Length: 25
Length: 24
Length: 169
Length: 161
Ligand SMILES: [Mg+2]
Ligand SMILES: [Mg+2]
Ligand SMILES: [Mg+2]
Ligand SMILES: [Mg+2]
Ligand SMILES: [Mg+2]
Ligand SMILES: [Mg+2]
Image (cartoon, each protein chain N blue to C red):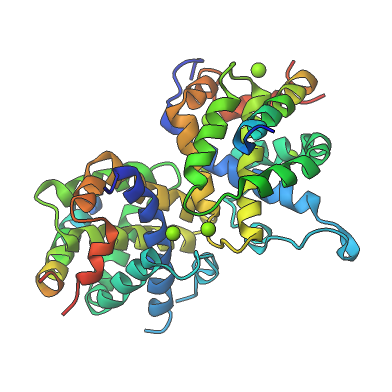
């Protein structure tokens, strides 16, 4: 698979964008 | 003198004492 | 006062205060009774905080409203961090690479919070593997990355961290 | 092969041990500052030893300056709002007439005394802010470079006599 530092950033961005969609008006 | 000026003065005095004592 | 005038250094000092409360109240809410969870991190359980303040509330509120989202990512981040094997020697380098990649397509409030979350998870992970006394280093990673990669300016241009108190459902 | 950013990271680690061992000494010479009594430190390391050793060998000098610095901090009345501003002014004046190892140590000492003073007056949770004052002042005003040019903080382990 991809290097863990790459995967972590992808999942942080995924999570961040979920938070933004839910809580940023 | 203002407290911050005296603090800096005493830090220089302390530091130079430390240096004279411990810097070979 | 008007938007645009706040300095990045003000945001940086505030970020340290926000991150401490984020860490404290996040760790507090994740604890479970009856020994069913991982042992608490005593450095986080007893982390000293400034007297109750608006910046402390920002950190606390972002931890609380993110709780459900955060818990859904627990198992995958635990796996990815074990794979990463961060150490005292490489934590800075890895933090920088990961944070840079996080923000490569833009900044938004959710991604800012995700950076706080990553700092929290990195600090907890290295503690669990025996690296004590490192929470201040991770806090510096967070603060300095934001300062040097435009995040502090993005926050400042929006009025500072207080603007995050409007995040919610 | 020593970068200023490496020296800055080491400064955070040096200062934490400096604070811990200095407070431990003061309390064995006023109510303890529990944030310093229970300050987490990295596992035994060279940088941790640097902080401990600089606190120990300066103990006699520091004790002789107790009354002067504690009184001047009471006069200064630093707060959460102005502490960094005063720190920067004082640190700038400390190094404007020269840099030497003793004055570098004096800056650590002032960081310790400032952190203890504000805690004693009710400002909890501020030790990280003061640690940042120390690290960032040194980094941004070329003291970290001065240290790096001497091989980094490990060179301070040769201070003694
Ligand atoms: Mg609240
Ligand atoms: Mg390690
Ligand atoms: Mg180390
Ligand atoms: Mg946004
Ligand atoms: Mg702010
Ligand atoms: Mg405040």
